[PDB]
Every structure is written in C-alpha cells, then in structure tokens.
Amino acid sequence: GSSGSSGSRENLGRIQFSVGYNFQESTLTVKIMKAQELPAKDFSGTSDPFVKIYLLPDKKHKLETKVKRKNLNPHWNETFLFEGFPYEKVVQRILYLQVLDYDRFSRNDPIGEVSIPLNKVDLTQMQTFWKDLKPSGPSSG
Image (tube, rainbow, N blue to C red; front, top):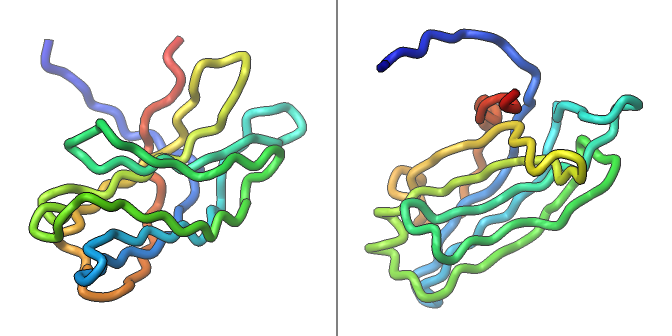
C-alpha cells in the first residue's frame, strides 16, 4: 500500500555546523558549532541531545559528538577528521547529521536529521550552514 500523506508541524529546532575539506592532507573537517531550539523529553524539560555524523551511503565508519545531560542548547564546537577518503570521492558522498536524545527507558528517540551533499558545499573552503533538523519521525507506538 503505497500511501503517506502527513503534514504536522513540530519544534525540532536547527543545527549549525561548518564544512570544509582539505586537499593537501586530503581530510574532511566537520565542526559542529552547537544546537538550538531543541525539544525536551523529560517532565521538567531536560534531555541529552547528541549529533551523529554519517558518510552516506557508506555506513561502515561513522562518527558522533559527545553527550550533554540536561542540555537542549549545548555547544559541541568539536572538530572531527575523516582520513582515508579522497576529495573525488568524499564529494560523491553526503553529510548526514542526526541529533538524537540518548535516553534509557526508550531505545532511541530521533528528533531530527539533515542531509547535504559534500559535492554541493564549496569544500574548497570552510563554509557554515543553518538547517532546521527535519522531522526524522516520531516515536512509534
């Protein structure tokens, strides 16, 4: 049954991050500034959000940022480096960033995610981007 017509609004917020690949070292640089407008899960209004990097399609080697408890607008400002991937390739890939809240009771509650082809972004130099964590889907029930 090929069906699916939904259009509900939600306050997932937006994620900020910088993109820039180096030629010499032939490595990728993904700096996750921070998050804002992140939804809560606990009664009081606290949650442990965390970004997850993925070089789609390939999902073998993946990276992620630390986890901040009771923090909806935490600042990661972390710097990662993916070695072993030539520009000519890294471009054919796509930058995947998902901000989920590490919870105990629930397995994993994905708030939102973002997809951006490294081929479109001027990897020639560091470039920032502001996207609104798309609705990765609610919690099945």
